[PDB]
Image 1: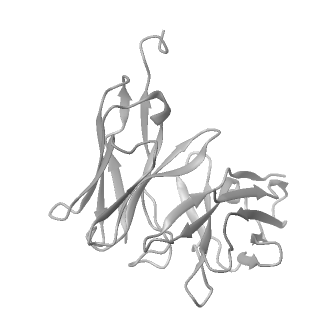
Image 2: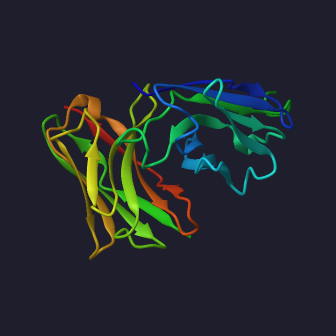
Length: 125
Length: 120
């Protein structure tokens, strides 16, 4: 029973920061290629970041390079996403997900999704 | 720039059929691994189907086994999703996905998405 439970989303002002968390149950995060996918209306889906090849190599989108940081905690079996210097363009629903071809399961699995919103004082008023 | 253009969505009656098409740009679907994701109203994204491996092996979710069929056409370089015996729960926004690994690690790509409404 592979399960990914997400946490950490919320409302933040530009320049703020969040730490998205995704706890896995049923398998070790130290063995799968994990990542984060953003979803926004009129934007489809895009891979934000990913950690792969338990040598531990990280991919980042050009939009989030230098600001986002993907991490693993094998003790707690949790994937982390540090999101500093947030922008209005980072507003979306983030999903922790496996690769298209998982090592454990024959088909990929997703998290439930966490809404992360970045809005300024002028946009809210 | 690798792109995935979806088409074929719309309204279908329960028990009907439909064929979602995804035209690829920047690569050949013959060598890559691809798949179909869907997002149901009030629910998160879910992997509908996939095709990967050197075997061309296909895999489906328990909800769509026997009813959905993923396939590739090298003639038009298009990924097809045949959906028969559509239920009301098949109403969703469908995206096509691909994985391209030119530098030893896969890179995920998605499409814009198309809406499929199984309504009476």
